[PDB]
Image: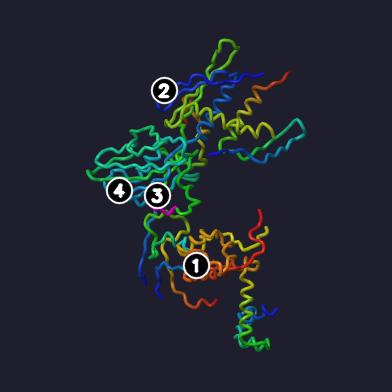
Amino acid sequence: GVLKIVKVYLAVKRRIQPGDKMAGRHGNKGVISKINPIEDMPYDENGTPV
Amino acid sequence: EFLKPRLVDIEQVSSTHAKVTLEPLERGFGHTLGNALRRILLSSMPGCAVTEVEIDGVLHEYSTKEGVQEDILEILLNLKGLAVRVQGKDEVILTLNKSGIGPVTAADITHDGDVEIVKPQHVICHLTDENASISMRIKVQRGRGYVPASTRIHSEEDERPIGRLLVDACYSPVERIAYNVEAARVEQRTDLDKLVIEMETNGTIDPEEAIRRAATILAEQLEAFVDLEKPEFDPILLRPVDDLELTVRSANCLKAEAIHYIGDLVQRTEVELLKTPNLGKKSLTEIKDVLASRGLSLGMRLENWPPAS
Amino acid sequence: TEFLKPRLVDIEQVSSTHAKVTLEPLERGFGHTLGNALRRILLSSMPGCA
Amino acid sequence: GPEEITADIPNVGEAALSKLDESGIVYIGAEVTGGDILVGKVTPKGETQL
Amino acid sequence: AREAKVLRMRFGIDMNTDYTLEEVGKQFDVTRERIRQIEAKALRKLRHPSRSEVLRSFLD
């Protein structure tokens, strides 16, 4: 029944957003809740944020 | 009753970072400022990051250029980190050309009056074959904050240059800002403190400029702080004339005749049009057909075009 | 690259000596820097006699 | 009837048809979003009986 | 009122079938070419927007 087919290939680039599942190798799952500005990140005395 | 502070020796250490200091600091104000400045320092500052890059034979960022070992995506990624600085221009397009086997650094671009390459050794990509050549249009603009390529397309409006690969905006001089208030004993005062703000940078901004504009915005925000249903005509009439999808010839005549919106067009008359330059019977025939197709015609009089805001 | 200053500022003040004021919109991150600092001065340094 | 991949599609402006070649297939490399026409397709339905 | 009847007549609006334009002339005692004209002005009258803003929003 099919005369012709057109397959289009899209490359979607997704970055990261609240709701994604993330986990370490230790069985600690987690789902990113908020995406924080660099300003509110806890930083050490040297000033390098976490 | 209070003491105002001011700067003192600003000690550059490397081309990247430096340590500025602020003496005249009263009791506890070292914190009141130091964090508030870090806040405005890390975020909102002026910066110039590469944005749109159109290259030679490359259709999209996912392809591979024959003769170069960097995937296009990777070359785009390298550019986001090219630090540059301009002076009197808010966007400039730099032309990079090079060929032959070897590293293509960031100094190989073509210099402009405002072009300052702060990292001439910065690697754009390698080149793997004797005759293999890469030409590229690199569009750098200046701005504030983080504008990812995603939000970049809303406006659109003929971004058709399929060859133009957008990249994400890195705009920011500041890398890392840290402040420490050590007690500064000025020869006479009870106890006053100092401020050692050690910052870190991509080399496109000087310490005094930053720390000045930082406090600039700060008080500028305190400014405010310190004190305390009837559409008439058819909406289609305010759509631009470009929405008619006329012939190249026909479209240019209307812009040339001061006819920019559909509302302007429906007023003009058949008689007038053959008298306007370049339009004959052939051109006019096209126009009458497209208008009937959207329920319009020529020469309708509106006693109130347009209203009223 | 011009900046953002806010608009509409409702002051709902309970009795006289008490007040709660809202000021919006700010640029992301600014509410906290403006807010905290204004808090530091008000608390730890203010002219007055008791 | 047979379905056509032709690029002549009822009720669409040229801006839609922009991203398409003459044939009805999106060009390689065109950046797209939701709603964009990847492939023009039209199937015969006769006598609409409006 | 005649423009409404003529258009409801010329189309099936709230009526069985629709009527050939000759039938309408006989119904109106004013006949033939005359009627076709009224139809035009009626469509013409709904075409230029005051009228037009609402019915255009139906297509796509």
- Verify CB contact (< 8 Å) between mark 4 and mark 2: no
Residue B191 x %, y %: 59, 14
Q: Circle 2 — which element?
A: loop
Amino acid of disc 4:
Lys
Q: Which residue is mark 2?
A: B13
Q: Name the quarter where the C terminus of chain C is drawn.
A: top right
Query: Same chain for marks 1 and 4?
Result: no
| Position above or below: D46 against C47 | below
Q: Name the mark on residue B65.
A: 4
Residue B161 among those drawn in magenta: yes
E51 up-or-down from C18: above or below: below
**Residue E43, how many percent across, how many down?**
61, 75
Let me know if marks 4 and 2 both belong to one chain: yes
Range of residues picked out in magenta: B159-164
- The amino acid on which the numbered mark 1 sits, given as a three-letter code, is Asn
Left or right relative to A36: residue B63: left
Write down the residue under mark 1.
D11
Give the number of the mark in front: 1 or 3: 3
Q: Which mark is residue D39?
A: none
Q: Kindly report the distance in space between the C-alpha atoms of the residues bearing marks 4 and 2.
A: 40 Å
